[PDB]
């Protein structure tokens, strides 16, 4: 049915389950990514090297999005939402990308530039894949206010 795509990034690894009907295309983009990523540095403690498997595909969500035009339909939007679903299912847990970034900054090493790059390229990939945020999430505090559990004021 599908052919797994192992995203080889030095010592950081994640496998991508890719259907065959687009595996020829996805296989072409990983061929380019290894050219774009620099070499592994001291366990990816560099300025851009992916230190956790999350940003390994996070930056993968970026360059694929860079090859997309939202107005036209192409062939890379098929792998765009493809890798997007796997990222949000594997590394995200129904929460927001902000929780993932803040916690990956909490438990693992802290390089806040990469952690913000994570939201930056994710949102571009998420919205650019014609997957808008036109669906409210159950952020605990806002549904708490809607239920009366709390109350908010916005100061500036």
Image (tube, helix red, strand yellow):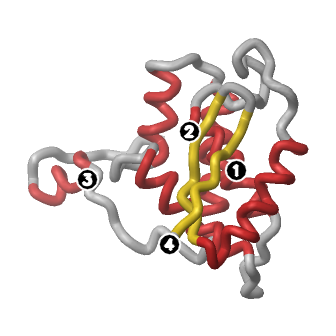
**Crowd tier of the residue under label 1, counting other residues whose Cα lies within 10 Å: few below 14, some 14–19, many 20 or above:** many
Work out how far the residue at label 2 is from the one at label 1, CA to CA, in angstroms: 10 Å
Work out how far the residue at label 1 is from the one at label 4, CA to CA, in angstroms: 23 Å
Residue sticking out furthest to the bottom: 72
Looking at the image, tell me whether mark 1 or mark 3 is earlier in sequence order.
1
Q: Is residue 155 left or right of residue 65?
A: left
Looking at the image, tell me whether mark 2 or mark 3 is earlier in sequence order.
2
Dividing the picture into quadrants, the one containing residue 10 is top right
The correct choice, above or below, for 131 with respect to 39 in the image is below
- Evaluate if marks 2 and 1 touch, with contact meaning CB atoms under 8 Å apart: no
Dividing the picture into quadrants, the one containing residue 70 is bottom right
Q: What mark, if any, has residue 142 been given in the picture?
A: 3
Residue sticking out furthest to the top: 42
SS for tag 1? helix
Q: Nearer the viewer, mark 3 or mark 4?
A: 4
Q: Nearer the viewer, mark 2 or mark 4?
A: 4
Residue sticking out furthest to the left: 148
The correct choice, above or below, for 46 with respect to 55 in the image is above
SS for tag 2? helix
- Evaluate if marks 2 and 4 touch, with contact meaning CB atoms under 8 Å apart: no
Q: Nearer the viewer, residue 31 or 135?
A: 31
Looking at the image, tell me whether mark 2 or mark 1 is earlier in sequence order.
2
Q: Nearer the viewer, residue 58 or 115?
A: 58
Name the residue that disc number 4 marks.
1
**Residue at (10, 47) in percent of width and height:** 149
Looking at the image, tell me whether mark 2 or mark 4 is earlier in sequence order.
4
SS for tag 3? helix
Q: What mark, if any, has residue 54 been given in the picture?
A: 2
Name the residue that disc number 1 marks.
60
**Residue at (83, 43) in percent of width and height:** 34
């Amino acid at each position: 049915s599908t052919r797994p795509l192992t995203l080889s990034h030095g010592s950081l690894e994640h496998v991508l389950l890719v259907p065959t009907a687009s595996f020829f295309i996805a296989s072409q983009l990983q061929e380019q990514f290894n050219k774009i990523l620099p070499e592994p540095t001291e366990g990816f403690a560099a300025d851009d090297e992916p230190t956790t498997p999350a940003e390994l595909v996070g930056k993968f969500l970026g360059y694929v999005s860079s090859l997309v035009e939202p107005s036209k339909v192409g062939q890379f939007d098929q792998v765009l939402n493809l890798c997007l679903t796997e990222f949000e299912n594997c590394y995200l847990e129904g929460n927001d990308i902000h929780a993932l970034a803040a916690k990956l900054l909490q438990e693992n090493d802290t390089t806040l530039v990469k952690t913000k790059e994570l939201i930056k390229n994710y949102i571009t990939a998420r919205i650019m894949a014609k997957r808008p945020f036109d669906k409210k999430s159950n952020s605990a505090l806002f549904r708490a206010v809607g239920e009366g559990n709390a109350q908010l004021v916005a100061i500036f």
